[PDB]
Amino acid sequence: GADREVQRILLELLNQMDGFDQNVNVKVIMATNRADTLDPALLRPGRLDRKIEFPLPDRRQKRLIFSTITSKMNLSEEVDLEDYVARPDKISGADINSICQESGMLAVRENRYIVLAKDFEKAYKTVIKKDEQEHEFYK
Amino acid sequence: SAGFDRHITIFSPEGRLYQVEYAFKAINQGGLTSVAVRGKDCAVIVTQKKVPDKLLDSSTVTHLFKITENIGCVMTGMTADSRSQVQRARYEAANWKYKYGYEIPVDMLCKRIADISQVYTQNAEMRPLGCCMILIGIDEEQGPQVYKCDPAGYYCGFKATAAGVKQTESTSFLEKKVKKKFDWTFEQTVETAITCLSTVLSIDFKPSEIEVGVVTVENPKFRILTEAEIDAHLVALAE
Amino acid sequence: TGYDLSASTFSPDGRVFQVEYAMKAVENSSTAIGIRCKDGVVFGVEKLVLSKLYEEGSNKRLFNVDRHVGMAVAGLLADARSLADIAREEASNFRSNFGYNIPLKHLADRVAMYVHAYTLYSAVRPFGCSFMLGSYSVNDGAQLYMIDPSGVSYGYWGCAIGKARQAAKTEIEKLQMKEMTCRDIVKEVAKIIYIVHDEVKDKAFELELSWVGELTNGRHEIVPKDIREEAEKYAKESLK
Amino acid sequence: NQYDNDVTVWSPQGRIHQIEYAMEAVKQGSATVGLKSKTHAVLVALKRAQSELAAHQKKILHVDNHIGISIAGLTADARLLCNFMRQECLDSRFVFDRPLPVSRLVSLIGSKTQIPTQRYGRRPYGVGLLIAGYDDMGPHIFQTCPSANYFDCRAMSIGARSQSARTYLERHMSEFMECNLNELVKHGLRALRETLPAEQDLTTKNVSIGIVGKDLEFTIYDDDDVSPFLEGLEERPQ
Amino acid sequence: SEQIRELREVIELPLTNPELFQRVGIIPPKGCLLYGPPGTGKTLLARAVASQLDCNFLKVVSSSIVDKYIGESARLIREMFNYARDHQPCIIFMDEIDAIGGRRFSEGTSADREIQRTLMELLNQMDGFDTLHRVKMIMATNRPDTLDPALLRPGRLDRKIHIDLPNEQARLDILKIHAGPITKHGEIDYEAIVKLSDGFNGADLRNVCTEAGMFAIRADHDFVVQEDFMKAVRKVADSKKLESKLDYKPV
Amino acid sequence: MADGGSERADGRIVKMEVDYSATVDQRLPECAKLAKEGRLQEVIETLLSLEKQTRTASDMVSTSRILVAVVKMCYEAKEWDLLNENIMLLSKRRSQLKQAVAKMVQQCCTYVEEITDLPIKLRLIDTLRMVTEGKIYVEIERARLTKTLATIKEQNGDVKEAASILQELQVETYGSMEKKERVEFILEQMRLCLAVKDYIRTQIISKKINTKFFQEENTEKLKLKYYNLMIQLDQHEGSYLSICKHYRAIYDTPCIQAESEKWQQALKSVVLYVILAPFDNEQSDLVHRISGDKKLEEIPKYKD
Amino acid sequence: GYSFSLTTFSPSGKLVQIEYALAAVAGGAPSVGIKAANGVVLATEKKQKSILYDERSVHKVEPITKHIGLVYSGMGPDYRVLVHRARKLAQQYYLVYQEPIPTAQLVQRVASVMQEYTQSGGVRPFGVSLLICGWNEGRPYLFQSDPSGAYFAWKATAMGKNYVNGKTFLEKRYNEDLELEDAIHTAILTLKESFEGQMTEDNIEVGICNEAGFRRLTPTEVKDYLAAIA
Amino acid sequence: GGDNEVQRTMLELINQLDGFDPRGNIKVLMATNRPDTLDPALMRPGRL
Amino acid sequence: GDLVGVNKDSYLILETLPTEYDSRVKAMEVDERPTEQYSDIGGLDKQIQELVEAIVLPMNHKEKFENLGIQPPKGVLMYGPPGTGKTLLARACAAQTKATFLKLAGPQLVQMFIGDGAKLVRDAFALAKEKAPSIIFIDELDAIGTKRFDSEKAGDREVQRTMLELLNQLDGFQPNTQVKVIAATNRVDILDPALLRSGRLDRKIEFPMPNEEARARIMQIHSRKMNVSPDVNYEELARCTDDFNGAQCKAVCVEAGMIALRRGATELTHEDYMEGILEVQAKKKANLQYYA
Ligand SMILES: Nc1ncnc2c1ncn2[C@@H]1O[C@H](COP(=O)(O)OP(=O)(O)O)[C@@H](O)[C@H]1O
């Protein structure tokens, strides 16, 4: 019981999306995590025409998110994030926010209006430090 | 979790297996920490003891174990599994001398020890010996060496070594220590082998709470230090 | 818990509860102590009468392994009997292969490795016993050993096994045992047994004292306490 | 209850329940009483009928010319230990050309029953042996248990409702070392009649008496020679 | 205190002092994660900062919010955030996230699908379509090795912070505070207590200060002697050693 | 057991001049072995600190002169050696260091008013260099706080002294007896940053202050030192109503301190430049508040 | 309920435990093998945790015979078992036939060894895939086994972490013939594709097969290739 | 966790089962097919 | 929640006369009730003294806890394997401590009335606060003491209203004399121990299974009120009992007397107790033809 209640909420969603009536001018925007899991009856076009994947960033889009966050920010240095555009070990777009947020904390933490580009590396190593043991084992 | 309950030694869908990596935290119930340092022609083991009772003796407590005349070791982890691990080490060191007619290298002995631990992972139906082993020895045309053998069957050779409870703290010191260019002239070695442990645990013994094994290319015999000369080096780094 | 059926499995923090469970089965056994003087080792067992039909020296816990080595077991008695036959058999092979008496430091190593092997496999269980080993020699002096169910074995000057393990060695350590003769020790063992729990929750008990050292010329045997009866004449003086 | 399945598994209290259950199998059999004087060791058992016309199942059984045993518990482990018992006795006759000491025979039984109490794949022996014997140092009464703890004793009674026999023996154990062969037997079978419900009587067809003596080979009596023993008794004090 | 100062920038300084975040130009009222083995400090830091310029602080044990019926665990989470939008300064505290935090996987058919839907309601009403404004969240769990990476990404739980049990010198600090307002003679060898004390828990150190008072009341003393502490240390160290399955393996 | 150390303390404090000073250093390792002991009731830490209290006092009698190099060199070689007969941590974290160093800054509080800059800044640096790397954690922290507040008054402020205190502010806010001592210490460096003309540095740390409001209740001179720096900070700018809002606090606090000219400086500063503010409704009601008063007619700028 | 044992099936498909063992291969160190026109290049990735670890103690590129080399991606301690197995098995050919064993013939037999641990029922399979190279009878060879027991022949391939990037790289990056030197320049370029840090002479380890035999490179040789490597 | 007119009957009967019955004269017998519905408060002596 | 008297049309409160209920809440008042000895309880003299250290010495030395600088606890918790020793020790507590005892059971709070669990919790506590020496007893608090990790707590709509209101009032009043609160449960492993922890139910008083001689005298006290044959071996009764509480030991004595009524015999026997042993856990024997 109650797992067919979940399953019938799908069916009511499939009906009022592609039933007889064809409710015009309504628009449906859906967003998930991993979408290989879900029902192929959703994924047929006529119902869910657009399939848009978001990558993490890549390079040349790290630059653009670096620009748009530091634009509204008193960076004002001659030490650039160019060293940190080209790093490997990819870094999701919400984390670029947190790098500038952590340096924003760490600029005021020593009572500065300004980011002095040694805090920038402390902010970088804070957000990226995750895999630490692996037991020197199974490589 | 995905939760296979990890009762026996099989895989998990993540790709790893949990029973062997539960043996790595089996060392930590010893409540102990050991350090090996290789700097120059000498190599130093240092390890504290813990005597909780006056009725308990002093001579029968030592974790320094002489394997051969020129190879010694120290054992961490739980006690009963550690001594049976030494018996295979003493046994297969003597088969080398019998079969092959010369003294076993310190590098080859860890291959034999790690392969015994590998079968207990690969084949089931024996508990995989929750203890760790650190060796020292002199090898001609190679200098001295330090090796560590894991319960998983992993071994590697490296200069500064920590084991026991406080690996990550002691190894953090020795990276900060062994990054410069020292020559490690046998009192440089022993002093840091104390002072790597002498940032960590905040203890203050009078000189009867540790053990120090040593080997040197002037006398390649394995050698356990005297309480008097332990006291000598304890005030020699130390003005 | 839910990880503690076999002795071949680890806990999620890294220990084996089947070894942990078997240790505190020894804890419910009666107290047996051991102490060594400067020229010998003196054993002592608090043993309680079952009902009345015990026949005054039945099922004793003071064993006799070799010419100069004996045990002071406590725990499951039948499990200690089979374990004592391992130690009897081990000393005979050393005699046959090397031609002299077994050293006690080597004898405890051979037994504890045999105890260790029952802590690994799922087909067998760990032993529920713990015991003492005392001996004496002219080339080695006196030694006193101690073996847990896990297999950890090293030397003491005095020890206790049973319920009152802590409550007995609290007053063993107030003795100047390094200079006493073992004939003085025998009346001093008698009070330590008699201090702890004569008939409080039990009814009656009986004292057993084993005895090895220079006065026995290296032999190991029971005391002549039928001779002179000096244990109970001196232990019962602590009523005040 | 999840720890209550195998002999191998310890409990979180330290008590293996499978050994504790084999103690209960001994209480399923009937009662039997053994005792000894300075010169004579007598064990007396109680038969039990299966039906009204079937024969009564025997309890006391001969082992050697100086050893006989009683039984309580499973008849499977009864003959299984008996065949091990008889084999060891004639080996000392074959090798050493002497009868066995009774005390060191029982130590072989404790080593025998120890192994199936520790390794997996074999149950303990649910059995209740009482042993009478003659070594060079006189009579002996021994009991065993499925926990392999063999006890030397001077009088013992095991089986169903055998506590009432033990309470009789404690207030008469001082009298046992001095009496002759005759009333020693009927000291013993005064103890079995308290292991009976008070409406039936100890007859000839339901009791066996085995005697081994200092100059007497172990002899089993049944149903006809019990009548010289059953004479000279009082009724039950009701 | 080293973690305490790092706690107070991301929580106290937004609601007390937004001008500093407008000089450099930066937002965050986000919230933390307190990871560390239990007993040390994971609630007092929440309660201390909920005294300094307080408002309607909440406490959620995060294990009373699950039951049989399926659409209720989401209904509690929706209500607790609507209360937070009602009273505009607000601090959310949810101990032991690991009960409902978890990770998503293939099939857990009966119970686990409710928990994941409970999670996705929590996961996307603190970073939902509505801007969670003037509201801060303190999540604290002793476990976390397995949490949802969507829960762990910065933007929702922007900075995590670790809490350790001993120092031998923070042991010195906690002991002097709980043996604060207690009458004595100043005969206090604090260090040899702390040397014998392997307490690992200020709750145990509170217990040590509690028991040493009780032995002083024994034999009718208006003061506390130093031996009352050593009786308290041996009792507490014994009572800890009489416990099993007490694993310490966080991330 | 420490009564022998008490009659050791009887022996030295009379015979610092009768006996030679290195004989006190010959009595040093016996009391240092007593400092090892500290066991149960008789030779314990509390009495062990007292023999250290006597030798530091007897050294300050000898080193009361410009020959100060005994007390500094013996104490450092003491704490080094009693570590060096051992490993990690001296004998106990509490007494032998921090009760003695509490007396060091107590003795430094006495001789600072007389002695010249040289042997005291040798004395202050040798208690700098011991709490930089050696005994540096809590138990205790405020002793170095009040020491570096005493270190800074030597050359009366320059570039070096402002940076000397900005490095030691950010830690000392965890506790530091927040009931005055932290508040007095945290307004001391903002005038220094005004002296080195760093204005953005000043207003960040000035923004820390005001949550300890109503500080006029128990003390009074804390208030005036705050706003006199606050009026100077905006004086390099121009929010002229903000100084006049500060001057209201400058107005009403010394009026109850019963001033007849000092109260008039606060009044005539208010009435001067609410005028200089640009026109706003905040200027309009404020001049409707501050005018029409029976305190205000004393000046012809009432008419202005 | 089928994911705990090995001797039984799933009602629809295949064995679960062998698929879980292949997940352990994906979590290993990256490795690249490229078959050139005249030789075969192996290359792997060797980063130690700390500075303390000696790099000259444990090796990855490992000879079996004088013309047969072998690398892996998986778990290191299981690797040492079947190396020592493949050593002793290579000699048994040579004792019989007095001739060096061809590279097709080991991989018949080594896979039959890894076969046998997939049997019932109290053993675990290996968590190691292999890459085997050799120059027998003029033409070189590059093979790949797996814990299931299959075995193949690649023009070029990659295994370990981030292999799908290296697959898409080498799919664009292979031709039919280059020399042995240009294979080395493109084998370091694909190891650099997924790397974290400064690639030095000790972070990588490279062995090759000439027709003149198998040899692994010294750090000086590996430095000078990595010096001016594109 | 019931309390809709079943417990009205139930709580009132267990109220009047004891309280008004020390040393009574009228015996009451219960009978059911389901041994699930045994109340230990009933099986506390005094009631059943 | 008052039963206020409201006008029909104006809907306005005219009178109240509130709080009218049924005879279960009337049955909760127990004062100056008969004497069970602490010395009747054997072997648990520690937990007797621990209770004196917990509650009686607060009443004795009311100011020694005040000048010292500590706080007397106000929540002491009894627990053990079963009862006969949970209620029975608490029956021994207020038998000789007369300071206005006030018992309260668990599901007596559980009504069909919503919230009148929490209403009765607070009003009885406030009534006990109005009494100056009164201590509060709570019986089977584990009936609502719940919230273990995965399977139990089942909801609910009465457990949370009674547990929280218990936590509401117990944090409300000050922990001095003499409004000490005692709860009686069965097992801590059902309860919430670390939630209480500070000023709530905090002192853990564990109980063991009683001993042979304790169970032997529990027989003879309970067998006083019937015709027993004066041939009773309590040594037989001591050892034959195993894994039995005094509740079952009382039950054995009553079942022995009921079997003597079945055959109409005037007296008992030890076998009648042995027959009672077979009756408690429902054993039944025969001849089983394995056993010769
Ligand atoms: N560093 C500390 N300072 C003050 N009190 C502490 C400290 N550590 C623990 N405590 C005490 O320990 C008790 C338990 O703390 P709590 O935060 O509930 O543990 P947890 O962090 O596991 O929830 C508290 O009552 C508190 O008084």
Image (cartoon, rainbow, N blue to C red):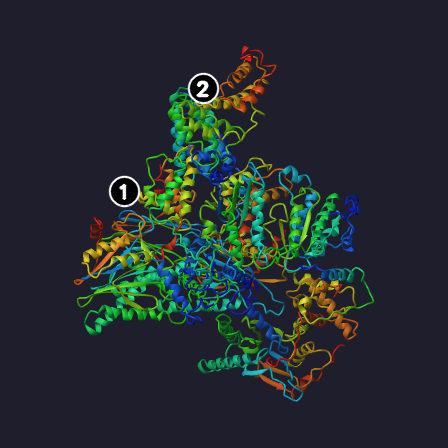
* Left or right of E215 in this view: A92: left
Say how many tags the image has.
2
The residue indicated by pointer 1 is B181
Q: Secondary structure at mark 2?
A: loop
Which sits in the foreground, D104 or I208?
A: I208
Quadrant the N terminus of chain H occupies: bottom right
Q: Quadrant of ligand 1?
A: top right
x%, y% of residue C110?
Answer: 41, 64
Please rate how many residues cluster around mark 1, counting C-alpha atoms within 10 Å: few if below 14, some from 14 to 19, many from 20.
few
G154 lies above or below B164:
below
- Chain bearing tag 1 is B
Q: Are marks 1 and 2 in contact (CB under 8 Å)?
A: no
Mark 2 is surrounded, within 10 Å at the Cα level, by few (under 14), some (14 to 19) or many (20 or more) other residues, namely few
Give the amino acid type for the residue marked by disc 1 in the picture: Lys
Q: Please name the residue shown 53% across and 44% down the image.
A: E202
Identify the residue under disc 2.
Answer: F113
Q: Is residue A113 visible?
A: yes
